[PDB]
Image (cartoon, rainbow, N blue to C red):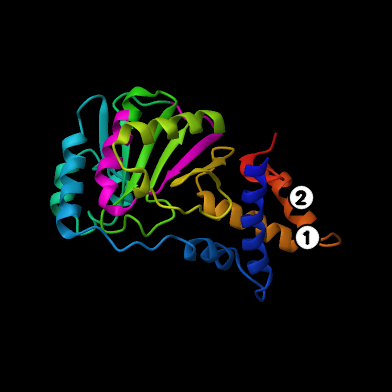
């Protein structure tokens, strides 16, 4: 409720900035969300290398696999050789990696997404904790982490994809924090627009209908719709656009009902 209010208000602010623009495109609206990313200076060269080496060390152990999310690798079924990709790809420090359980878990059409924000110096530690948590918790279908050169500069540097609701995410979040060994001050105070803050560095949002546009683009498009409606206050149009698009009109982070 209080959670819902803070979340809606950041969504509404975003929407007002979109509304102030002249004939804004969906992409324009989306860039406002992208522009609001945290902007940490990257971890050092050695820290990046330690990150890649940890990925390779994690891959294939304790029920976990790590695969590049590089599109070319994926479609060619080449994403199954982590060590070779890191060795050769000039994008290895930049692209996303997914952390998956050895035995694939079916995704619900409606998933929760837990976004985790730590200082880039702790990315490796977080990644280890994510792998352990994914190993143990079958509610989590997979995780993803951005390459070490970009960790701390994206709205989505680290994400867990969860079959479950906000309560399940809260529990996994508190679990992640207590088990990671990462100092509490090292979590980054930042909540992406229209996501619900669970605690410092932990933000939650829900996706529907098997959506894969991503949280920013999906909520950007709710705003576009509201802008296209007429005859009602802008505030009511946003709430109506949320409902009509399947989200909770009082908490844009959540599915409707």
Query: Tag 2's secondary structure?
Result: helix
- Which stretch is magenta? 106-132
Q: Residue 157: image x %, image y %?
A: 37, 51
Image quarter of the C terminus? top right
Q: Is residue 165 visible?
A: no
Q: CA distance from mark 2 to mark 1?
A: 9 Å
Tell me the crowding category of disc 1: few under 14, some 14 to 19, or many 20 or more residues within 10 angstroms, Cα based: some
How many marks can you see?
2
Hey, which quadrant is residue 57 in on the image?
A: top left
- Taking the image as drawn, is residue 211 in sight? yes
Quadrant in the picture for residue 153: bottom left
User: From the image, which quarter does the N terminus lie in?
Assistant: top right
Reply above or below: 120 against 31.
above
- Where is residue 40 drawn, in percent x and y? 34, 61
| Residue closest to the far right | 231
Q: Is residue 164 located in the magenta-colored stretch of the structure?
A: no
Report which residue position mark 1 lands on.
229
Mark 2 crowdedness (10 Å alpha carbons): few <14, some 14-19, many ≥20? many
Residue beneath the point at 20% across and 28% down: 61
- Which residue is painted at 32% across and 41% down in the image? 98
> Which residue was labeled with disc 2?
240
- Residue extending farthest to the bottom is 22
Q: Earlier in the sequence, mark 2 or mark 1?
A: 1
Is residue 127 covered in magenta? yes
Q: Disc 2, disc 1: CB below 8 Å?
A: yes
The percent coordinates of residue 166 (x first, y second) are 56, 33
Q: Secondary structure at mark 1?
A: loop
């Amino acid at each position: 409720k209080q959670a819902a209010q803070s979340t809606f208000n950041s969504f509404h602010e975003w929407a007002k900035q979109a509304e102030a623009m002249r004939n804004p495109s969906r992409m324009d609206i989306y860039k406002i969300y992208k522009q609001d990313a945290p902007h940490s200076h990257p971890m050092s060269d050695e820290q990046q290398e330690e990150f890649l080496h940890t990925l390779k060390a994690l891959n294939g152990k304790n029920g976990i696999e790590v695969r590049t999310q590089d599109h070319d690798s994926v479609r060619n079924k080449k994403d199954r050789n982590l060590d070779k990709y890191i060795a050769e790809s000039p994008d290895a420090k930049r692209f996303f990696y997914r952390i998956i359980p050895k035995h694939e878990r079916r995704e619900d059409k409606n998933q929760g997404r837990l976004t985790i924000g730590v200082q880039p110096q702790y990315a490796t530690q977080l990644t280890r904790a994510m792998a352990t948590l994914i190993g143990k918790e079958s509610a989590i279908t997979h995780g993803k982490v951005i390459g070490p050169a970009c960790h701390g500069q994206m709205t989505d540097s680290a994400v867990l994809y969860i079959n479950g609701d906000v309560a399940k995410a809260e529990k996994l979040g508190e679990k992640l924090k207590q088990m990671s060994g990462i100092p509490l001050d090292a979590f980054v105070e930042h909540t992406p627009l229209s996501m619900q803050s669970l605690s410092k560095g932990l933000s939650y949002a829900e996706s529907i209908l098997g959506d894969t546009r991503g949280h920013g683009m999906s909520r950007a498009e709710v705003i576009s719709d509201a802008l296209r409606m007429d005859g009602m206050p802008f505030l009511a149009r946003l709430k109506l656009s949320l409902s009509a698009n399947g989200y909770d009109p009082d908490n844009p982070a959540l599915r409707n009902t």
